[PDB]
Amino acid sequence: HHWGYGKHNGPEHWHKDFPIAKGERQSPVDIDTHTAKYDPSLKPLSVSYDQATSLRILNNGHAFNVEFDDSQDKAVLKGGPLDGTYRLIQFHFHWGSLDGQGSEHTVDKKKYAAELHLVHWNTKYGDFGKAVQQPDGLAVLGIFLKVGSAKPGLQKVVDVLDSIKTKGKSADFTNFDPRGLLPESLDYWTYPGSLTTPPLLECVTWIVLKEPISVSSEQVLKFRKLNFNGEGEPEELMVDNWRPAQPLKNRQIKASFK
Ligand SMILES: CCCCCCCCCCOS(N)(=O)=O
Ligand SMILES: [Cl-]
Ligand SMILES: [Zn+2]
Image (tube, rainbow, N blue to C red; front, side, top):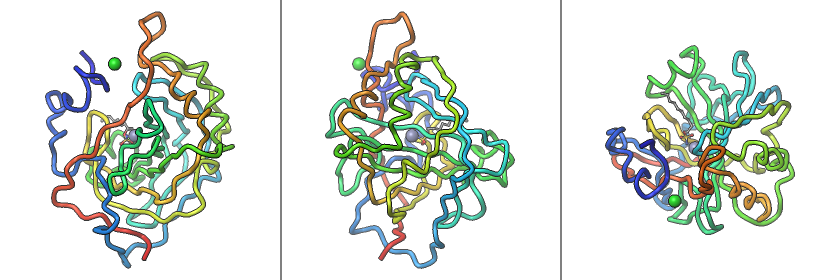
């Protein structure tokens, strides 16, 4: 009985195996734009993905991960609310069964069609494993997806999904440039949170971009053709793999823009 997004193993069940699910800094959260406050102490955000080197794409039964070689100082996120440098290790998405839902974070309760998560770990901790044992071990750059014009830079990801339809399948995925998934503006909201999937560790500094990227209906429809199940098992489409907004508790969301 592994965790998932179904009626008997979904978000409302996670707290039993992962008590931190009801913690003090859980993610995602609803971003109340009027309550968010501009923070002058925030330094310029720096996203340097020029030397990013992807290696493989994997269907882990919950979503698909585009993995990067993080053995060297490449693809780093710094500045903004961050102290030090964070290295990109992988990115993945959360999406819905319909265009009207899919994102984890919401903006004034608005749900986007999907949400992209670029996961980075604080280099001061040596590697990802040690970083997830620290309150400032991770930084996730979240980007909303809305349905409209196609995102050219996402097509290579879309076209490889047919080869990793089921849980456990992976495929070579080199030379993918994540810069092609970024919106024009880097305006963002930030707050201290957690991983949105078990183990739900509270080690994340969330940086959620205000400007969504547009993807075509055809592109997201292909995301929805993936399977939660493994090969040879009854088909359960990989859709609605998002955790709903959690209590904000003793936290404040800061804006990088006035
Ligand atoms: C402690 C070992 C488990 C670490 C698992 C990390 C999964 C990270 C990806 C899922 O998180 S999210 N949605 O970006 O917040
Ligand atoms: Cl189901
Ligand atoms: Zn995620």
